[PDB]
Image (spheres, coloured by chain):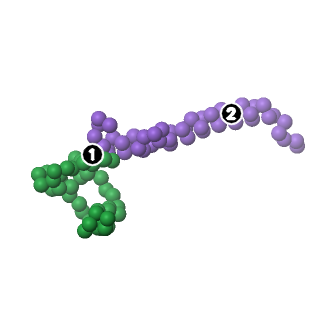
Chain colours: A green, B purple
């Protein structure tokens, strides 16, 4: 969708693997702010937003 | 019969207890950081910050 109509999705009740996202080279910019990119496999959250 | 005649010792004890209580309560302040518990900071982000 357009930038002024950005598409929002809620993710819950799942087992997420961020390693497969991080190791891929398809992404030009991979910038995480509040957490370290390599520690995402060691944390548990709820109500993720994309 | 009459109580509250020993206010000085009570005041000393109360002052000591209050000082200890505020000292232990001070541990729950952010001080401008992202968290008040050190384990979360250690386990959530990469050392250089």
Mark 2 burial class by Cα count in 10 Å: few <14, some 14-19, many 20+: few
**Identity of the residue drawn at 68% across and 33% down:** B15
Q: The C terminus of chain A lies in which quarter of the figure?
A: bottom left
Q: Label 1: state its secondary structure.
A: loop
Total marks shown come to 2
Depicted B16 relative to depicted A1: above or below: above
Q: Is residue A13 visible?
A: no
Q: Quadrant of residue B33?
A: top left
Residue occupying the far left of the picture: A25
Give the residue pinned by disc 1.
A36
**Disc assigned to residue B39:** none
Are the numbered discs 2 and 1 placed on the same chain, yes or no?
no
Image mark 2: chain: B
On the image, the x and y values in percent for residue A41 come to: 24, 52
Q: Residues within 10 Å of mark 1 (few under 14, many from 20)?
A: some
Residue found 20% across the figure and 58% down from its top: A17
**In front: A13, or A33?**
A33
Identify the residue shown where x is 84% and y is 41%: B3
Mark 2 or 1: in front is 1
Location of mark 2 (residue): B15
Q: Nearer the viewer, residue B42 or A33?
A: A33
Q: Position of residue A31 (x, y in %)?
A: 24, 48
State the SS at label 2.
helix
């Amino acid at each position: 969708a357009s930038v002024y109509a950005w598409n929002r999705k809620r993710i819950s009740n799942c087992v997420a693997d961020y390693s497969v996202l991080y190791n891929s080279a398809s992404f030009s910019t991979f910038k995480c702010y509040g957490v370290s990119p390599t520690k995402l496999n060691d944390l548990c959250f709820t109500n993720v937003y994309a | 019969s009459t109580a509250s005649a020993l206010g000085k010792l009570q005041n000393v004890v109360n002052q000591n207890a209050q000082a200890l209580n505020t000292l232990v309560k001070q541990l729950s302040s952010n001080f401008g950081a992202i968290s008040s518990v050190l384990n979360d900071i250690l386990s959530r982000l990469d050392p250089p910050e």
